[PDB]
Image (cartoon, rainbow over all chains, first blue to last red; front, side):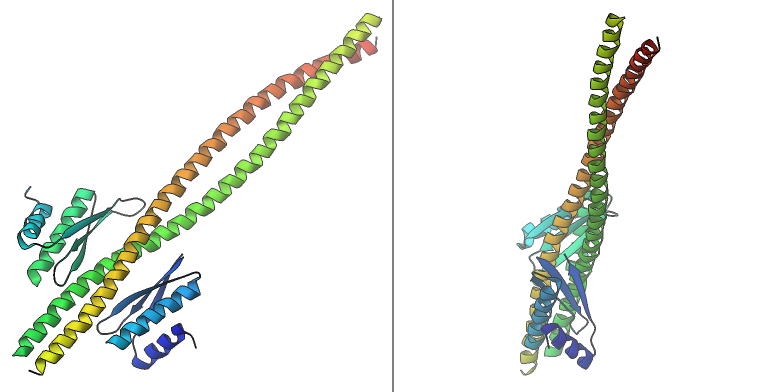
Length: 65
Length: 71
Length: 87
Length: 87
């Protein structure tokens, strides 16, 4: 039910690839093979929190297109 | 000299766009890296690699000039 | 005809993005490798600090063994000389 | 004239994508700088501790030579006292 889960639901639904890259705050870069493609980031106190912050920023961007 | 880096600066003074170099030493990597930013419209973030900071800077400058000409 | 202009704008933004993403790419690859490098050095530092701690303890054992030897020699000498003086 | 709405829209989406992406690039640049620095740091720390460990091993060996001399001295004292006891 998390942000990450929404984005993955969305990528499975609209057929674009989503790749998380985690960096030890924690940093997550999330790449989206959309048109045009997106590269978002998120930070957090854990890999999970940063991944969901990234996913959230991706969902915001996707909605603004 | 007369270099790539000099041509780009000539161009930035001429056309009033900002250009910023960022250099990364070889360190434990396979080569030197330079990122160069161009405050153009749309702005550009180019890079260059080399066996020296001088080389990576010229490679970057060159990358920047190619992209500017292709617009 | 406004479409020539549309497709041109699209073209220049595509060039800009492609280029920029190439930069992002080299930054990510180097950052991944650097992070791996840091974990390796962290582990190696740990092993050598362990080894140094161990050696420091050994030095303390050897130092104690040596003072024990000095006291034993002093006492032994005192004994040998007392028996020499007795005979 | 409708083509201008779609033109300005596409432009808007590319501008958004680019802004977002450049913010990511900046994050990557800082993180790569810091990681590279850490690699330098741990590499240097590693040499520092190996060198310190090396000086410590030499101290150990010097003290070991000390103790070796002491043991021979003590043994000769013992042989003296025990030979004198036997006479």
